Amino acid sequence: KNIESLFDYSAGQFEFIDHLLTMGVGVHFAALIFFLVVSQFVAPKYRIATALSCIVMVSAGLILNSQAVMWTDAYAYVDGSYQLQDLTFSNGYRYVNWMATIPCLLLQLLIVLNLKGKELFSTATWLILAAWGMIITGYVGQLYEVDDIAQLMIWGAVSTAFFVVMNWIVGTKIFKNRATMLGGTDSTITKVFWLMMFAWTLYPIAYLVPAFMNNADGVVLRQLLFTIADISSKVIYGLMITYIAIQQSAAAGYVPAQQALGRI
Ligand SMILES: *C/C=C(C)/C=C/C=C(C)/C=C/C1=C(C)CCCC1(C)C
Ligand SMILES: CCCCCCCCCCCCCCCC
Ligand SMILES: CCCCCCCCCCCCCC
Ligand SMILES: CCCCCCCCC
Ligand SMILES: CCCCCCCCC
Ligand SMILES: CCCCCC
Ligand SMILES: CCCCCC
């Protein structure tokens, strides 16, 4: 079970969560349109980094819309508060989105990093492997967020071990391949790494909400952190990857990338 199913919610708490999720759908699909449009101004060897953002926007947007539908269908406003009608709302569908979107977010980083060939394939394999372990162990720990907080923290500790290893591999490859990047994007890519580390750390914090704020307000706070983390890790992060791909495109002489930057 999950802590969401434990509480009734005031109209203010319930509708705030609903608007957070609905706004998340709108923001992800709004970025989707932008990424599709701007991808033509990216050189062919970087265009797959922009395509990966489109895939992330589609899958993140569809699953956020599924959760807003489940949120509305699970509770009804009875006797002055929103009460659970159906055992249907699960944050586990976020975990399947994460397993879908995390590899795409990692791959588009490696591409603008100018990883190629054997090093690109092998690095992607280990990063996806480390992400798989982080998601599966975290998903099992999330099963005990109501019944046994101790198991939530023990599985979260193992999941964090995968998280630290994944970031070490990413930081290692950035430090090693920064110099190959054009147009000053070698400076930009490590700030993207800092944003990635800040944004991805918001997820384990929301994961631990049942352990330090197990009430209706903690449920609101958790969806708030997820909303901030999604927009940061997918939309803002994707905009920076796209800027890097366009900047390196223009630096290599790709003409339509140069007009796009001339407008700003
Ligand atoms: C768009 C969604 C993204 C980038 C999700 C990222 C998720 C994580 C970095 C998850 C991290 C976790 C741990 C490090 C420990 C506790 C369990 C997890 C799975 C929440
Ligand atoms: C040419 C670069 C392609 C990069 C794609 C790498 C895919 C490697 C797949 C590794 C298998 C990991 C299985 C974990 C998923 C459950
Ligand atoms: C690129 C170098 C980044 C180094 C960051 C080190 C942060 C260490 C984390 C300590 C725990 C913080 C938990 C919020
Ligand atoms: C937990 C953050 C790991 C950062 C790795 C940096 C490695 C650079 C050589
Ligand atoms: C309640 C509005 C949430 C918007 C979060 C945006 C985060 C950007 C860093
Ligand atoms: C840059 C080579 C294409 C990447 C395929 C995932
Ligand atoms: C070069 C791929 C990194 C290996 C991680 C174990």
Image (cartoon, helix red, strand yellow):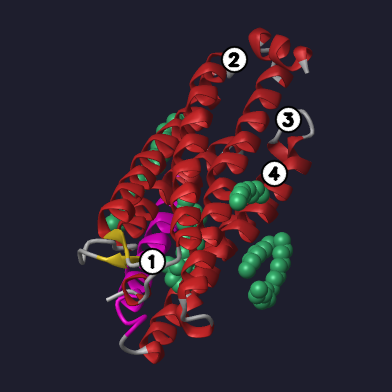
252 on left or right of 37? right
Residue 165 seen anywhere in this rendered image of the structure: no
**Residue at the (54%, 37%) spot, across then down:** 111
Q: Give the residue number, with chain letter if any, for mark 1.
A: 81
Tell me the kind of residue under disc 1. Ser
The quarter of the image that holds ligand 3 is: bottom right
Please report the bounds of the magenta region as a residue range.
Answer: 120-146
Task: Tell me the element at label 3.
Answer: loop
Task: Tell me the element at label 1.
Answer: strand
Residue 30, given in percent of the width and then of the height, sits at 51, 29
On screen, 5 above or below 101?
below
Q: CA distance from mark 3 to mark 4?
A: 11 Å
Q: Using the rendered view, name the quadrant where residue 55 is placed.
A: top left
Which quadrant would the C terminus be assigned to in this image? top right
Mark in the foreground, 3 or 4: 4
| Front one among 82 and 103 | 82
Q: Neighbour class for label 2 at 10 Å: few (<14), some, many (≥20)? A: many
Mark in the foreground, 1 or 3: 1
On screen, 256 above or below 195?
above
Magenta portion: prevailing SS class: helix
Q: Which mark is residue 182?
A: 3
Q: CA distance from mark 2 to mark 1?
A: 51 Å
